[PDB]
Image: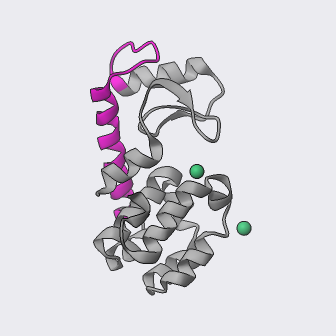
Amino acid sequence: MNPFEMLRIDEGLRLKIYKDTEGYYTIGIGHLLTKSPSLNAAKSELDKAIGRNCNGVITKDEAEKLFNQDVDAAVRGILRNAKLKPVYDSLDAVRRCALINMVFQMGETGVAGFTNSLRMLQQKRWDEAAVNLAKSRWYNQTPNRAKRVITTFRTGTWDAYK
Ligand SMILES: [Cl-]
Ligand SMILES: [Cl-]
């Protein structure tokens, strides 16, 4: 297990544009295209992301690529964020995967918002942090996935992913 396999499990892989759990246009491995309702605004975004006329369809290789960009960006924003960095640095290797996962899904800004959970993780209060993370729209909206990440923070193992 690693951050890539982890996210691959959680996001899946789709080669035609689809609508995510929030009803937004996405493609590949959780690559948001646009928050706009317009199928056309998405197809445009697609083409500019990929560098070809895609006609809303892409290849495995092309999804893998955007994915690689997206992970790197998640990591680079954790590192750049004053609230996120100290947490990430304090965590072990497994738990680092879980913060990457949340950042990818909700963005740096969104996660930095979880002030209290962040403090508890940094302080290594696992049980507490897991109870607190669960009191969130995030948990209520995608409970199977939040449960996976939460257990990851809780136990520091990949069990929820096996
Ligand atoms: Cl709640
Ligand atoms: Cl879910």
For the point 39% across and 49% down, the residue is: 7
- Point out the quarter of the image occupied by ligand 1: bottom right
State whether residue 83 appears in this view.
Answer: no
Residue 53 among magenta residues? yes
Pick whichever, 13 or 23, lies toward us: 13
Eyeballing the image, is 160 above or below 124? above
Pick whichever, 88 or 61, lies toward us: 61
Residue 18 coordinates in the image, percent (x, y) = 54, 28
Q: Toward the viewer: 68 or 142?
A: 142
Counting from the top left corner in percent of width and height, residue 49 is at: 38, 28
Pick the quarter of the image with the C terminus.
Answer: bottom left
At x 52% / y 66%, what residue is drawn? 112
Where 47 falls versus 97 (above or below)?
A: above
Snapshot quadrant of residue 88: bottom left
Residue at image location 29% in from the left, 70% down from the top: 93
The colour scheme of the drawn protein is one colour
Please, which residue is most extreme toward the front here?
162
Quadrant in which residue 97 is drawn: bottom left
126 to 76, vertically: above or below: below
Magenta span includes 151? no
In this rendering, position of residue 24 left or right of residue 29:
right
> Image check: 86 left or right of 148?
left
Quarter occupied by residue 53: top left
Q: Position of residue 36 (x, y in %)?
A: 63, 30
Q: Is residue 41 above or below residue 32?
A: above
Q: Main secondary structure of the magenta part?
A: helix
> Residue 160's x, y, as percent?
44, 63
**What segment carries the magenta color?**
50-79
Give the quarter of the figure containing the N terminus.
Answer: bottom left
Q: Residue at x 61, y 76 (%)?
A: 132
